Each structure stands twice: as structure tokens, then as C-alpha cells.
Length: 235
Length: 235
Length: 9
Length: 9
Ligand SMILES: N=C(N)c1cc(-c2ccccc2)c(-c2cn(CCN)cn2)s1
Ligand SMILES: N=C(N)c1cc(-c2ccccc2)c(-c2cn(CCN)cn2)s1
Ligand SMILES: [Ca+2]
Ligand SMILES: [Ca+2]
Ligand SMILES: [Ca+2]
Ligand SMILES: [Ca+2]
Ligand SMILES: [Cl-]
Ligand SMILES: [Cl-]
Image (cartoon, protein in one colour):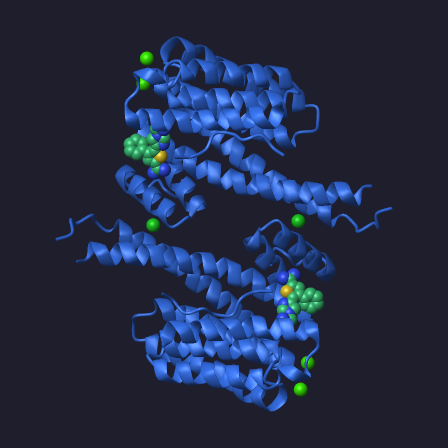
């Protein structure tokens, strides 16, 4: 890899600089290089990895949605405009799939298999579910069902560990439940499951807030508010 | 070039789609491909070219400024942090210089030499001044003076044509004067020249507004407001 | 309107 | 504060 000659610590330092400069493609390349050193990642490093790729794929998803909407309008009384909209939507889609495959490849080689603590293992399995979910958003072929089931399976394994090993207010556990609820609503055509999961997650977190410091309370309630916002949109 | 196999019209169509999707690197690559077809550019196409590269270089400039500030703080009681800040600032700087060189190369091969009408020739010479100005922002070596003079010379030629061939409210003429005033203030250490140019430009445009339609009035006054905002900051 | 997923810190 | 240059349409 092009980062093979750079020290691990320098890659992490430069990822932090890239974040400050809003250079998320660079940030992701630095963090990929750091993962490829073969050592496990600390909590801060795991979050740097996620921030970088979430920003990269987030821009791709936003662009894909714009282009997909234009394409769908073109396929209604609509003047034929040639293959260009489809071609360019396909170009962005292929790039997005490539980023998702890269993240999934890092998780499979070898972040998940070396992650034994709940905070690392749940984090990575959640990420696996997320990037399969992003693949599912653009999937249409003989693979859509299998991609959806791969997302579901990763989220389910993460959920099972999180419920056994983490308190209901743990921010990773909350973010996982939030994203699995989004999977149910937006991917799996299961709005009732989404609503039930969001409600139970919110209520069980509410009942555990009394155990938390001021700073942890702030962290947990911020994520709980997203559960509440979705419940307001969904009901 | 990778765009050599794509039709000119398809490149323009995809540049417009990339703009809508906020994919400015793609937009710039499409417009570079369109320029390399060898035909002159229409007014709309010239603006697509400028929008694309302005967005690309604008992100690079913003990142370079963040990194340069971090580097300068590191070189004051400041703990030594190694070569990483300098290296990464240099990486972004080199990328930025490469984008500027690409735009300057398109202008030199062969957009300027084929531009005979004032609206095209002034537009391209202004762009030449702008991209030399962006090079000057990061220049430090035995080339800073020559880069500054290249920006000045391009802006001056554009100014001379614009004053002979365009009314004082023409939006290209106004944007040129605005950017040349910024050159004087921020690059050439000539704040009085900047102020004088902004004032004369604003006043001469004011006196020509009566000749304009409602839509042209809106276009011209929007740029005049930037001249006024700078004068407020500079005085 | 699309559902809200987990946000960065 | 940095000077304002020409803006896109
Ligand atoms: N450079 C960034 N963006 C981040 C840095 C850290 C960070 C993590 C540990 C120590 C110091 C900083 C982040 C973090 C923490 N948690 C916890 C769950 N709420 C979520 N994100 S994020
Ligand atoms: N796709 C974009 N961004 C743009 C398209 C056009 C455009 C130009 C001609 C015809 C139709 C559209 C732009 C334009 C025009 N002028 C004039 C000076 N005020 C500045 N920009 S910009
Ligand atoms: Ca381990
Ligand atoms: Ca535990
Ligand atoms: Ca000509
Ligand atoms: Ca004229
Ligand atoms: Cl394409
Ligand atoms: Cl670097």
C-alpha cells in the first residue's frame, strides 16, 4: 500500500490533521494504512477510522441519491436524454461500492477476528452492518437479498453481544440499536420492528441514566435524541 | 486523457450532473475533457469550467490554511512534533499547485489564444490571474516574485480589455476588478491600490445601473456588494 | 424524510 | 478576516 513506508504513529497523527482540514479521503487513506500495520486499534483510533469512512461514503451516498432521483424522473412524458444519467449514476455507485468493499475488507482482514473486548467487537460488527447497509441501498440484482441478510446478521451478532456485555446507555450500544432500527425501517421493509427497537432502546436507556456522570449523561442523551427524532418521524 | 473517448456533449451533460451532485472533482475532470476536444467554449461552458475548478481549489486552499496555521503554531514553547505537519501541508500544497498548473495549462493550450471576443478573452485572462494568485498564496521560494508578476500581468491585460470593450456594470468586468483588488490587498502588499480600485469600480458601476434591465441590475449589484463588503473590511 | 442514523462525535 | 473574492452564480 502507498502508506506502507509511513510509521503507524505518523499515519494516526496525519489522520487527525486531515480531519481538522476536512480532508476525509486523505483521512481514510491514512487510517487504512494504520489498520494495515496489523496491530489492533484503540478506541480513539477506531473512531478515527469510522469518522473518515463515514464522511467519504456519506458524500457518495448523497451524490448517488441526487443522481438516482434524476434518473427516475427521466424514466417517467420525459424527453429521452441518452445514457449519460445512468452512466454517471453507475460511476458514482461503483465508487461507493468500492469504498464499502474496502471497509468490509479491513474488518475481515483482520480487525473483527482480533477484537475480543465488547467495545471493540461490537464497534466493528456494527460497522460491518453499516457498510452492508450502504451496499443494500444501491443493490438491485440477484444479490440484494444476500446483501441485506449480511447486514442483518452483522447487526444481530453485535446486538447479542451488546445486550450481554454493555449497559443500556453505552453509546456504542445506543448507536448500534439506532442504526439497526434504520436498517429495519429503510432497508428491510420492517417499520414496526424499527419502531419497537427504537422505543425499547430509548426506554431502557432512560432507566439507566441515573448511574452516569454528567459527561456520560450528555453522551448518551445525545444519541437517545436521535432515537426520539426517528420515532417522531415514523409515528 | 481518460475523457478522450466520451462525446463533448456528454461531458458537458455530466459536468452539469456532477454540479447538482456536488461532485466537483468529477465536474472538473469532465470540463477538462470538454476543453481538450479543442473547440472554443460557450459562455455557459466557461462558467461550468470555472465553477468546477473554483470548488476544487477552494477546498484545497481552505485545507492548506488550516495546516499552515497548525505548522506556524508548532514553530513558536511549542513541543516538537516531528516532520508530519510539514509533510502533510506540503502534500496538500503540491496537490493544489497541480490543480492550478492544470488550469493554467488549459488556458495556455489553447483557450486564451483562440479567445477573440471580450467576454471570452477577459474571462480567461481573469482566470489566469486567479490561478497564479492561488499559486502566490503558497509560494515562498525564488519564484514568489515571478508568480506574483504573472498574476499581475494577466489581471492587467484583462483590465485593459475590459475597460475598452465592456460597460462598467458587466459582471465579468466587475468580478475581475474585485479579484484584482483582492490581489492588491492580500498578495501584492498594496492595500491603497486595492481600496482605490474597489472604490472606482463601485462608483462607475453605480452610475451605469440606470441602463440595465431588472435581471442585469440584480446580477451587477450582487457583485458590487462584494466590493462594498471588502471596502468595509479594509477601511 | 429519511431516518436519522448514528452521528459522529 | 480575509477579503472576499468573486463568487459563483
Ligand atoms: N477525532 C475524533 N473525531 C474523535 C476522537 C474521539 C476520542 C475517543 C477517545 C479518546 C479521545 C478522543 C472520539 C470519540 C469517542 N467516542 C465515545 C462515544 N461517545 C466517540 N467518539 S471521536
Ligand atoms: N451551471 C452553472 N453554475 C451556471 C450556468 C450559467 C449559465 C450561463 C449562461 C446560460 C445559462 C447558464 C452561469 C452563469 C452565467 N453567468 C453570467 C454572469 N453573471 C455567470 N454564471 S453559472
Ligand atoms: Ca484482541
Ligand atoms: Ca461490560
Ligand atoms: Ca475565437
Ligand atoms: Ca462591448
Ligand atoms: Cl460517467
Ligand atoms: Cl503526507
